[PDB]
Amino acid sequence: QEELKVTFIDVGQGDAIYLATPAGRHLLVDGGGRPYDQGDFDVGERVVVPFLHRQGVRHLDVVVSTHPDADHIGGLAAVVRGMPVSLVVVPPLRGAMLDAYRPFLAELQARGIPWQEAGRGDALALDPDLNIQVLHPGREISGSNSDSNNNSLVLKVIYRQFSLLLSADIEAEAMADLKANGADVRSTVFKVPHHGSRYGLEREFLKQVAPQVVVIPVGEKNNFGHPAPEILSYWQEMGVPVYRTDRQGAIIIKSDGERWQVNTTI
Image (cartoon, rainbow, N blue to C red; front, side, top):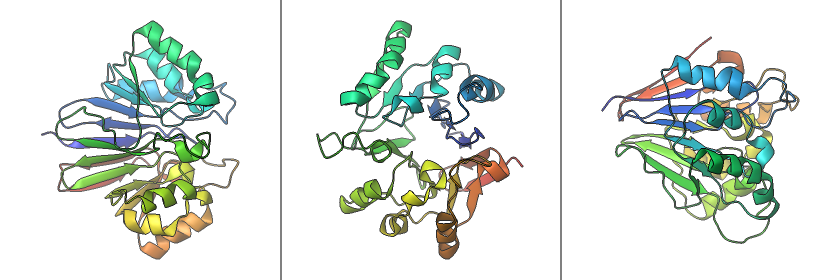
């Protein structure tokens, strides 16, 4: 019954979220995403794996690759090459999406690392005190299975009264679907999708999340103007503090399931 500790690693314009669970399990959600820095600097080798060593991690129980487009795998390649990984979770892979993932999945097979496709209604049993629910995407052969950002994996991490919604890169169309299907998205902490892009502004969905604080992993002087002013304005309208990795470095959230705290690096 150690506290849950979640670190949003400062990986620039990218997401990498390390969760140390109460029982002592190690979970990594993403590893920096698509290299907009042309990949010459591998954020996985240079930032993520060294971070995990500095936190004392020697193996990861679960690695989650949230995005169905394989050129978003990014630093996760370096993670599975740089330390033992017991399980990789990916979204439902279909069509050309599976195609592009095939080299990564072949490396997993060569390493003996099982992978699991996860979709709406699944859960990642890892720690008996943590409920890790997969809310999105569904598995239906539906319209635009190929709609990449909107079919990224959404996870809700629950420890008693504390919850964290890891929204990956979803946009307003996915948010409307989640709202329409009654997804239980109300959360203590909301990870804003796709670095605060304005295309994640779905007010009915965000009203239901009703977060106490939000976290934006986002890079300084990224090419997209992230986080969008419309997104920052929205959280101001709601009175919700915004934590950002570009301005504040790594963001650390700790909780015993009743009390929780957010701290920053810079």
